[PDB]
Image (spheres, coloured by chain):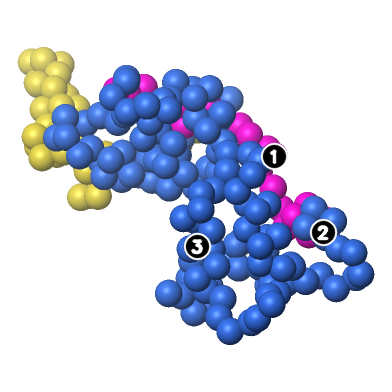
Amino acid sequence: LYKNLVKPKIKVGNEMVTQGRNATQVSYSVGGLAKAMFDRTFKWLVKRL
Amino acid sequence: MADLKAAEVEKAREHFEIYDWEGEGKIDARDLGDLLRSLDCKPTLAMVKKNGGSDKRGEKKLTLEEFLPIFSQIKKEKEVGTLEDFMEGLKVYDKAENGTMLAAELAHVLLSLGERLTDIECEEIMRVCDEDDDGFLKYEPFVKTIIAGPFPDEGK
């Protein structure tokens, strides 16, 4: 879990670089996973309903 | 293609963030010289100005967005140098097959042609030597300490 928020994996085509996010960006980038997750529970309900 | 790895991006960030003396995130075009040098790419001032650099101070300022398309160009150079070129080169002094070099004769070659060193830097290059009169250095320990750097095993 933790690590990847601060220091991501950026694969640009054929090259991969680890580099740099921030404080507002960790409590953006965790959602992030809660961007996918919230909008997929939203979409899960949209489907279900 | 080539592009900068996570480790390399950290090397480039650290040094740049150090060079921000102002508090705005920028480097001078003069300071482009020793910045790349600390980044460990070894260039001529000719290589520095080739990518937008200055003799003078107070000319142009470059961001990291500018600086990285400098550094990712610089990495292409192949002819950096080895040891053995320098051996072959510094052997030419000989006259009697001794590999030994008199002090005046050795300061003068450092001063005269090239990007050049000063009077002052020659006083420093001599500093490590002690207690040999009329007055001989030697080609092999000399070159090896240059490539070894400021702290091989000992270091002052």
Give the vertical position of B102 relative to A42 (above or below). below
Residue B134, magenta (yes or no):
no
Q: Residues within 10 Å of mark 1 (few under 14, many from 20)?
A: few
Q: Which residue lies at the image location 66% right of the left edge and 67% below the top edge?
A: B103
Chain A is which colour? yellow
Residue occupying the point 71% across, 53% down = B82
User: Residue B115: image x %, image y %?
Assistant: 58, 39
Q: Is residue B155 left or right of residue A8?
A: right
| Quadrant of res B107 | bottom right
Q: What residue would you read off at disc 1?
A: B79
Shade representing chain B: blue
Residue sitting nearer the eye, B117 or B4: B117
Between disc 1 and disc 2, the foreground one is: 2
Tell if the residue under mark 3 belongs to the same chain as the one under mark 1.
yes
Q: Quadrant of residue B69?
A: top left
Distance CA(mark 3)–CA(mark 1): 30 Å
Foreground mark, 3 or 1, reads 3
Which mark, residue B93?
2
Q: Please provide the residue range marked out in magenta.
A: B61-88
What residue sits right under mark 3 in the picture?
B123
| Co-location on one chain, circles 3 and 2 | yes
